[PDB]
């Protein structure tokens, strides 16, 4: 592999792993469209299983990018419109605060303060209906962004209703299969369990627990190869043969809202390239990423901008993931780790690598 890539990756990631005490890590760099892979450490410390290119990691909220694209694909199929009221797809949602809340608001965290998490107490479908019916918005729709699993998770569940497919069936048939992501899963099958890394939290081996809207908000597991392929697909959607999927990918990178120097897509978030690295590095810190922020509507949304830093962070209890790419440069990176370590360290390392190669 080109020595420049080897050197920039190893010189950045080796110290990262040491500083953050990350048990296992995989990195893919997409350079001029081609992937290059790097692995370190352990998928399972107790069983001495190394990280390989076939190791599954929990993506956490990087799953939101799959949800956004699947939603985009449903728009392209004509099954849903982002302008459609939430109640069109969930008629039981009769409470008056839902008047004016559209699928766009759900997809982009702008419904008016839907909470970061669905309460753990919500176990049944009746529980979920009660939760949304009883929720009281802090703000009018389309005025403030508050990053939330309960927002985009509901979008994902509603987006697949017209198809009649379960969220998982829709994801597999309409996104995973066409892109040949054959080692990407919402539920890890028994056949693949030998490859499923443990996450590590406070030294304990952990996997994500079941929760409401988990598949839709944070539930995808994948390998570094499949994730490199996901980045390639999002870098160059025009190479994708399935028309509605190609279109869905483009819709997910459209710019719907602006807050500061960031633009909200469907799942993806974007900044203009060249970026100010302090802006994305500091902006990734949950102190900022999870805050309530006023948004400016982009009316109408700007289609995907090639000169963008497009990215998403993800975490579960035991895992930390990051994906970033720059379409204009045919350049991208995926970093998957089995420890949830601070976001700014992820973005700093990714920027150091992509900047050196650009």
Image: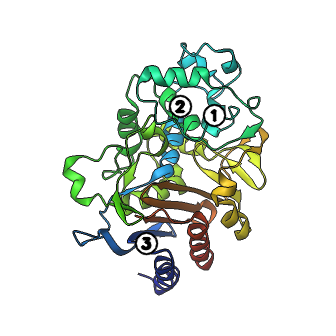
Residues at badges 1 and 3 in contact (C-beta under 8 Å)? no
Reading the image, the residue beneath label 3 is: 22
Q: Which residue is drawn at 70% across and 57% down?
A: 271
Q: Answer whether residue 246 is visible to the viewer in this image.
A: yes
SS at mark 2 in the image: helix
- Residue 247 higher or lower than 161, as above or below: below
The image position of residue 273, as x and y in percent, is 71, 64
Reading the image, the residue beneath label 2 is: 154
**Residue 22's image quarter?**
bottom left
Q: How is the image coloured?
A: rainbow
Q: Residue at x 53, y 80 (%)?
A: 12
**Viewer-closest of 111 and 249:** 111
Reading the image, the residue beneath label 1 is: 114
Within 10 Å of the Cα at label 3, are there few (<14), some (14-19), or many (20+) other Cα atoms? many
Q: Residue furthest left?
A: 191
Q: Which residue is drawn at 66% across and 44% down?
A: 254
The image position of residue 338, as x and y in percent, is 40, 64
Q: Distance between the residues labelled 1 and 2?
A: 10 Å
């Amino acid at each position: 592999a080109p020595q420049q890539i080897n050197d920039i990756v190893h010189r950045t990631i080796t110290p990262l792993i040491e500083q953050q005490k990350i048990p296992g890590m995989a990195v893919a760099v997409i350079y001029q469209g081609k992937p290059y892979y790097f692995t370190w450490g352990y998928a399972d410390i107790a069983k001495k299983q190394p990280v390989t290119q076939q190791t599954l990691f929990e993506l956490g909220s990087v799953s939101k990018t799959f949800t956004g694209v699947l939603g985009g694909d449903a728009i392209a199929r004509g099954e849903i419109k982002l302008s459609d009221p939430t109640t069109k797809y969930w008629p039981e949602l009769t409470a008056k605060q839902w008047n004016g809340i559209t699928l766009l608001h759900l997809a982009t965290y702008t419904a008016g303060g839907l909470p970061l998490q669905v309460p753990d107490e919500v176990k049944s479908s009746s529980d979920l209906l009660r939760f949304y019916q009883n929720w009281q918005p802090a703000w009018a729709p389309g005025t403030q962004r508050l990053y939330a699993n309960s927002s985009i998770g509901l979008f994902g569940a509603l987006a697949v209703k017209p198809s009649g497919l379960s969220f998982e069936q829709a994801m597999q048939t309409r996104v995973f299969q066409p892109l040949k992501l054959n080692h990407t899963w919402i539920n890890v099958p028994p056949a693949e369990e030998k490859n499923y890394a443990w996450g590590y939290r406070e030294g304990k081996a952990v996997h994500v627990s079941p929760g409401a809207l988990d598949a839709e908000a944070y539930g995808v597991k994948s390998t570094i190869e499949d994730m490199a392929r996901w980045v390639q697909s999002n870098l160059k959607p025009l190479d994708i043969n399935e028309k509605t999927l190609q279109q869905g990918i483009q819709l997910a990178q459209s710019r719907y809202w602006q807050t500061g120097d960031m633009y909200q897509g469907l799942g993806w978030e974007m900044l203009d390239w060249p970026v100010n690295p302090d802006s994305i590095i500091n902006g990734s810190d949950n102190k900022i990423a999870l805050a309530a922020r006023p948004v400016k509507a982009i009316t109408p949304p700007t289609p995907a901008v090639r000169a963008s830093w497009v990215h998403k962070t993800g975490a579960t209890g035991g895992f930390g993931s990051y994906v970033a790419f720059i379409p204009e440069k045919e350049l991208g990176i995926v970093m998957l780790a089995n420890k949830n370590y601070p976001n700014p360290a992820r973005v700093d390392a990714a920027w150091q690598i992509l900047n050196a190669l650009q």
